[PDB]
Amino acid sequence: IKTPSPSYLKGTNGHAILLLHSFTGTNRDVKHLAAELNDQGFSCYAPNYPGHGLLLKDFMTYNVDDWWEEVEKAYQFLVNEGYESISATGVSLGGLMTLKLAQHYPLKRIAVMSAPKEKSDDGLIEHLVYYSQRMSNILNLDQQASSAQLAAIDDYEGEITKFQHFIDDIMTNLNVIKMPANILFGGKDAPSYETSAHFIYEHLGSVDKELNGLKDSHHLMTHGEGRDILEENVIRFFNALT
Ligand SMILES: [Ca+2]
Ligand SMILES: [Ca+2]
Ligand SMILES: [Ca+2]
Ligand SMILES: [Ca+2]
Image 1 (tube, rainbow, N blue to C red):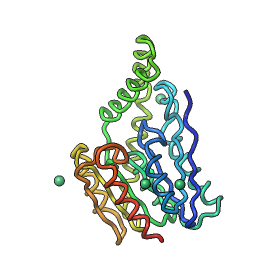
Image 2 (image 1 turned 90 degrees about the horizontal axis):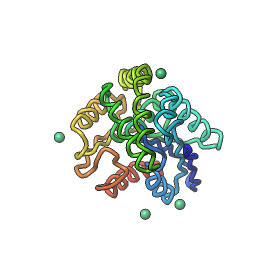
Image 3 (image 1 turned 120 degrees about the horizontal axis):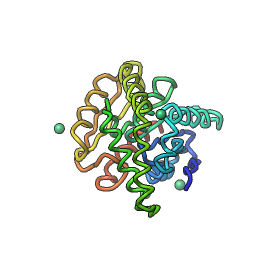
Image 4 (image 1 turned 135 degrees about the horizontal axis):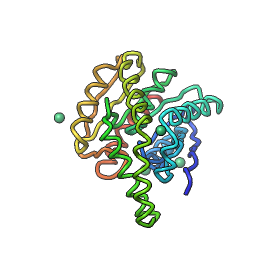
């Protein structure tokens, strides 16, 4: 069991795209979309947030500051590789990281999928519970371990609060984001994500922005039903760079 390594696809057209995964996901969330973008000429880089891929008790020794530092590091990696054109896309937490990147750096364009405008403590705890169960049926861990993993959740309360403030600080300052933006949500996701997408769209500073609700897409828009429609949309959006 280890955190996956980053994935770097070198392309030919001189433009680079960061691809950022979901909360409790890994960079396998974005593998297919990265591959399809690379087949259109783009260089693609998909980091993995620290702690992601590990058992819950190890996962919770990392926090949103660690995850953001890794995203900063991934941006700098592309700068150091010589790319003058860098763009970003991400799903769920990765969509939040994309928005934050755009507040800090001169990204060329951004595509944001399934970003929330706020998260409750129950909602985030519920993500962590599902993560630990999926992992126990994979790793076929005994019953005793599973329960201890979930009992450590109580000590993460301060880090949940930090994550909530992280979201609030991004959402307060959407007006400083000015480059072209594609805001996407799934019509088979919770209705709060449609409300979030409208909020984000309406508060962005960008003059060149679009809102795309995809009726067949679920929360993890890169996977499952509707994925072909999502990919065509995102690829069309980034191909405007060429
Ligand atoms: Ca293909
Ligand atoms: Ca390829
Ligand atoms: Ca703690
Ligand atoms: Ca609607």
